[PDB]
Image (cartoon, rainbow, N blue to C red):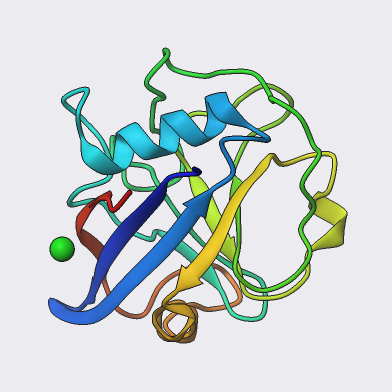
Length: 164
Ligand SMILES: [Cl-]
């Protein structure tokens, strides 16, 4: 079936717990595979040790820039950027996992976990999974964000990988 992956997250160097994500490889196989491989690190790079650099309460928590740690970087397993696969899945509510981007066909490695329904992103960002377990951890991360997106604690993915 669809992959299950995990992110273990610290805030200011102490663990918050684990976020478990189901990746909708049946719907968006290419997008799911990129994220899966970046969690395992099997290509020699990926999310381990990187940060949630942009977190906005009552919106979303954004991560995945493992090259520049600031929203300008990241790369996919395919190359620097890859196409929007489809917009079939929608930003239905809290726990949606979706690709950050800088316009059409600019997916790399950055992603976000929604903490509310974000319908205006439908048709613009590729949704590719959702939180199975660990919304409590997501709410903790969210609580360390701000209107500007600047975090008030350093939020680090210490470990990540594939469960099934
Ligand atoms: Cl484990």
